[PDB]
Amino acid sequence: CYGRSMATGKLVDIGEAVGIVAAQSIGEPGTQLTGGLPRVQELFEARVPRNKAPIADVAGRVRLEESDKFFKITIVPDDGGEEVVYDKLSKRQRLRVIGVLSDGDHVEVGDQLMEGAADPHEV
Amino acid sequence: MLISQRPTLSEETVAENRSRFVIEPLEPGFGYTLGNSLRRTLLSSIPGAAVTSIRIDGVLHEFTTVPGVKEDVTDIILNLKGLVVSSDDDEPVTMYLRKQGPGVVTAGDIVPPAGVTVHNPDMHIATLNDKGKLEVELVVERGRGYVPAVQNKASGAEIGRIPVDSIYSPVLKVTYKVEATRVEQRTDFDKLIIDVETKNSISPRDALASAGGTLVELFGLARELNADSEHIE
Amino acid sequence: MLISQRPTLSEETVAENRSRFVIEPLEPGFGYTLGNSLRRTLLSSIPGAAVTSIRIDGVLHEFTTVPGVKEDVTDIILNLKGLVVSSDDDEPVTMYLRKQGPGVVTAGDIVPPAGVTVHNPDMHIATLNDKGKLEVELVVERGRGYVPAVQNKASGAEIGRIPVDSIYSPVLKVTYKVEATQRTDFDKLIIDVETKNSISPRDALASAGGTLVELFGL
Amino acid sequence: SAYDTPLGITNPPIDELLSRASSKYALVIYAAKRARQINDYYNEYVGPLVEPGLQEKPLSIALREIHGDLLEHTEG
Amino acid sequence: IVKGENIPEPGIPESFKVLLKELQSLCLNVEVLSSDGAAIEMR
Amino acid sequence: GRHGNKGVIGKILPVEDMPFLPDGTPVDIILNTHGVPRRMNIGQILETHLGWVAKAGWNIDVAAGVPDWASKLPEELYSAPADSTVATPVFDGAQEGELAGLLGSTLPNRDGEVMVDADGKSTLFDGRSGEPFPYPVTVGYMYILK
Amino acid sequence: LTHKRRLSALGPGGLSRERAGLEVRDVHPSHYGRMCPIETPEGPNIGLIGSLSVYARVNPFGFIETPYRKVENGVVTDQIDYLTADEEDRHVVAQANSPTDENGRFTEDRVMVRKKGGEVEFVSADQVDYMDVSPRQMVSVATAMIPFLEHDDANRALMGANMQRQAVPLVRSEAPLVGTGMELRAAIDAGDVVVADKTGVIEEVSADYITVMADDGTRQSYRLRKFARSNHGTCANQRPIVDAGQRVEAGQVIADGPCTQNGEMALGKNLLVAIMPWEGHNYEDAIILSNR
Amino acid sequence: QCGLPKLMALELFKPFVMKRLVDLNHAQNIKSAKRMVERQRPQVWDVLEEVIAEHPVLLNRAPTLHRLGIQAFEPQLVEGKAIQLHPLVCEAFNADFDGDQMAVHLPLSAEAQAEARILMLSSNNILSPASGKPLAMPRLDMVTGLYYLTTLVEGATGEYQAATKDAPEQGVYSSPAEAIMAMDRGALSVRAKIKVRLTELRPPTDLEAQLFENGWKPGDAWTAETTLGRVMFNELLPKSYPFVNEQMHKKVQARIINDLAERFPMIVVAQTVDKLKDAGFYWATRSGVTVSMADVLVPPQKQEILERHEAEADAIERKYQRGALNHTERNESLVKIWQDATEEVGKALEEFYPADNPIITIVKSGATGNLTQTRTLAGMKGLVTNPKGEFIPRPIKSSFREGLTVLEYFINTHGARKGLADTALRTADSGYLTRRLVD
Amino acid sequence: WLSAASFQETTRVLTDAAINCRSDKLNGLKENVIIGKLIPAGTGISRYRNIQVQPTEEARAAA
Ligand SMILES: [Mg+2]
């Protein structure tokens, strides 16, 4: 399951402690990380993202609406079941890209609705 | 004045052609000082006979080719550059190689004039296609070092005259390195490793002593000035 | 195409301390390897002619001053480094220097024993005033190269002796150059040898060759 | 294979040693115990199954022994 | 090393013995148990 | 040096085998070329050139007139003897134009030959093999602290 | 000399090294001519420690002032007025080097100026009030000692200043072949050099002491520090640069200090340098030396 | 191997030698042995070399980031008080010779020495155990040394022609040993285009099938066209390896050494790289790479380009001076005007530099440096950031070649310091992350 | 529990451990480091450290 040892170039040996090696392989370049160590730390610590971005709750076409200062996204499920609404999306975050999401685009169960960092707990 | 202890000269034999030589210990920094002069004395200074110019029958204004042989003009010249024969003439002598019919020519088919002796008969020269003949003249003059092909005057009047790069000296490759001894009786002393690949004319030991003498007497020009100051033996 | 006109080494003169030397002819691609082979040996193995230790009555070590002398003992040792001496040797021999009253001390004021000489008496050692008195003996040994001061804990010396770094190098500055001999080109190199006046460029190049000749063997 | 000639610690080559044991870790205990075994003899008791070098260190010996397949081992 | 014998097997680090003592001084009862026989004494 | 360039002494060679100028004058320090370009300390190369200027002296540039570069302008600086010391206050120092003009100047070692060109380079001879180094190398005098 | 003149934000009555953020470490526009921006520690003291600038001067109330030359109607006077940071935000500071005209006045059509932003601007000679006393007002003493400073990135310059104060006195103490202004005045103001306070002539010169007979009829003598051990173990040895007969003037330099030669700071030696890479010996910042 | 200061070695091994010189009768009892080592009587040195032989030691440099920060070597007694570190392990240790120090540790028990020789030995750890890429691979000097070796120069000395009419080809050599005799004389250039017969090297794949295909060239002779250096380069690779015949960038060197690890034992790669080192240095010095105010070139188009955007700036600034322009837009516009010009000067600069210049060769070969770096040296350093983190619309028009100005310099440090402060807290946080990953 | 204590929030950890009356099996490698045991990884794993070595009877013959 682990696969080849990057050092030997062959199947990993049975003694190898790959956790420590993973820890070091990840942290060593951290000095070169200038969207950086804060984002990395954000991921490994599983905190809710800096600017939360919503993910599709279900599959269906998307109805886009622009309020004043906000965005409204509604997913009409292919069920077709209960419509699913995403209430106030600050226009500062814009939207994710396929190009940029537009009214009528289809969406699968996991897709990211807006540029940002999806809450890992939510996914 | 000077006494020091102690240098010695030993040799590891890699092949009948090749030998490695090492001198231990030197006094720092004498490795760099002499070693580069030795690579030169063996390479450029040793008397030996080599081919100078050649002309083939049937090649005059043609660029490269020889009907009846798979080897072309260029391939045969460098094929011939490897010919090793010690000549006693001191003046250019023309040997002759003439052969016909299907067959493979070798350095044994060439008839040396009296005083020139070919040291590598098995040497391959050309492959003769079915029903073919080859005629070649070879100019062999003594010399030293490596003298690139000379067009002087230049090749000039002679039509079909091909000057060739002449490897005059027996030793075709040499290199040196420097390492340090010792166990701290002598700490960081220099050890010189010299790598000599030789042609069958002379052995490595012969080419070393030849360099030794040509270099020793060479420096006699300076020692004759006084002889007062000296060193250890 | 053997060209044998045996190498010719002819001397020259430029100044009294240095003289050019020329050797012709030589096979192509030589003078460099042959020139540097002499320069390397000249800048190192020419024997001397150097001062090992020194003793000054008043001072027990290098780091004090002397009454009335302008230079501290360490800045005086530095000056005495520039001494260019020469000795028939063998075995160590002590020189002597004593000067009183104002003036300026120089190498001329050094009284050498029988069999040694000081070749730049013009050299400034220390400047003394009415109270200044300098009594110092110097030990000249013979050798070659650069030998760092031998500490008297390693030697058998007592607390008084000041060991000093010793430079035995008759030769001062050395260079060379070559000029080929067009086809048929040979090589002729000229070497420029300068000495400190402890020996002539002739005698040193003789030393180098003599030292360089004995080394090549087979 | 021509790798030229290994000097000192690099002889014998790991690769030729790793064919004599399951992993690099096994190779360590393999040679390691044999070395403690040799040193005892100079005062288990057996070996130097190979011809000792002049001053050769027991660990260096045990590695040569392993290279020549002069000993077998059983993993735990 | 001075007798050229084999290097012996290691013992317990003194710092660890100290840690147990420092935890005891906090009213933390720290026992080192074997597979059994239960409590081992550091001494 | 004063520019932030630092390093340990990795080796010290017999004065016999060192890059040495045509005079037979050995160089004291050999600094690696690679550390220089990426560190933005290039001032250390300037003072390496000026260092050679100040050590060897120089002349104008006159007559007939004063050249275009000196016009902005070195004053009484037209000539300095060998070994004279220079001062380039930080934010008004010597300027690139003025360096080149000075870089050619002045012989001799002793003999009338010149040891450095208008590029601040010279042909060094390897004191090891005795043969020259194939390309012209930058030489000069740098101020380095212990 | 830089240890005095150091100003640090740590200590009792000030913030701790750990708590203070990078806003205090950044250089402010008002540091100009007061606190040298190019000089601070590389460690995690960066920006908390700095050295007072060359012409900077402290106010009786504790605010740093910088010298300026006031300009009126496109003409820079000889009036030199020391202004605090508050009164500098009040006016327009002309650039130190702007072309000078005959008896002096604005030559260049327009003037380089600093605003109260501080935000730089280009306006004609019309609106200026004060001008800079000279370049390197912003620079500190050690910084002002880097030849060709303007060509080196602030990163390597900082390292360069720090390492000058890291050098050690040599026995010989040779002065820099290519220098800057400060070497002269930084050595005398350091106090490690022997200066004469009255014009006169030298009665005696010994390694131990130097006496001068003033024109005043008074007699001054100076005992020389000899092989004195310094705080960190360097050598404070001094040497006389004068001879018995010599005439001398007030404020002149009688004897050299540990790092000085003939009155100017000598922190090192002038060496013949070759910038070629050499046989993998000087590599990765390593250096090779002549056994000389 | 590693250079170990003999004084340091003596103390490290003290109990070992104390035994040895009691075994040999140098000292009668252990007490005498101890004094013999302390006073450093000359007999001990020969003894030290005995005990230290094939007895490994661990070398560490702090901070230790990956396990490669500790490696075992074979100690060699060295004069002086410094430590001689192989130049190919700098990468792993991140070792600067600016005065870094390193710790030495002496493994004692048989198991510890085994772990050193087998697990941690220098030559068995080559590839990074993260990306698998090679680490000990040549770098810096060794790049430019080989890059120069393998490069091909149009119209160099001895260039094969090939001859026509009255002359044969003229660019051909009996053997590689001949092209050397030609190179030592002024005839041949190492970077020349000549073709040669090679008995002892191995041709490529395609040219292998067409020439032999029986078949192979174990002792056989064959001819290809390459630079003399490219020949000597391939003499460094294993005899079994095919003939590459390229000029070696760093990446090209990475390709090959990556390939040696897949197809060959480690010992082979260990020795191959050792040979790349020796060659790369010899030719890095013969490379003729230096730096000079002269070798720093500036594009002449910089002036016009500079004043070209000066108008666009003062005009867009003229549009803001008119009052219509949005202040944030005018400043923002100055960013785009100047940011763009910085590329043109980069484009213009790159276009100016002859390909053999020493400054560009360093960056081209991948040894060290950037173009962004060589853009600030000559041309323009470009826009810089205020401490607030924004972009100061005032560009630095000068480059560090012409020198910056009082205000140009004061502005640069504004940002340049904030970066050097970051580098401080980037190791403090990165290490705090690594400690959590590890746990 | 001693692995957690050495990591962070030592006081919080020790207090919860003493109340839960926690027993640490000393399986992990950090625990074995603290007490000086052989970490259960690499050469310290059972299969490797229990290796038994003897020369082949064929080898002993050649002596
Ligand atoms: Mg460092």
Image (cartoon, coloured by chain):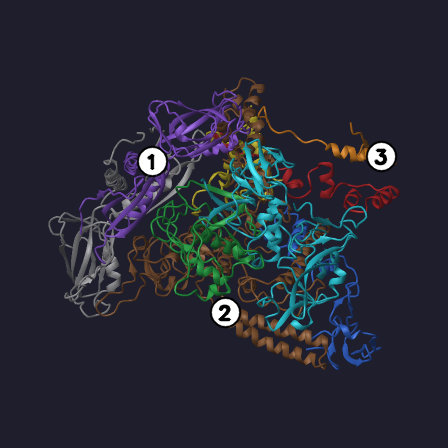
Chain colours: A blue, C purple, D yellow, E orange, F green, G cyan, H brown, I red
SS label for mark 1: loop
- What label sits on residue E23 in the rendered view? none
Is the residue at mark 1 in contact range of ligand 1, meaning its CB lies under 8 Å from it? no
Quick one: SS at disc 3?
Answer: helix
Residue G6 locus on image (x, y percent): 70, 48
Q: Quadrant of the C terminus of chain G?
A: top left
Side (left or right) of H346 relative to C24:
right
The chain to which mark 3 is attached is E
Residue drawn at x 27%, y 65% as measured from the top left = H169
Q: Is label 3 on the same chain as label 1?
A: no
Of G257 and H343, which appears nearest the observer? Answer: G257
Same chain for the residues under marks 1 and 2 in the image: no
Badge 1 is on which residue? C197
Q: Are marks 3 and 2 in contact (CB under 8 Å)?
A: no
The quadrant in which the N terminus of chain G is found is top right
Residue D22 in sight from this viewpoint: no
Q: Which residue is mark 3?
A: E24
Task: Quote the CA–CA distance across marks 3 and 2.
Answer: 76 Å
Q: Which mark is residue H299?
A: 2
The span from disc 3 to disc 1 (Cα, nearest Å) is: 85 Å
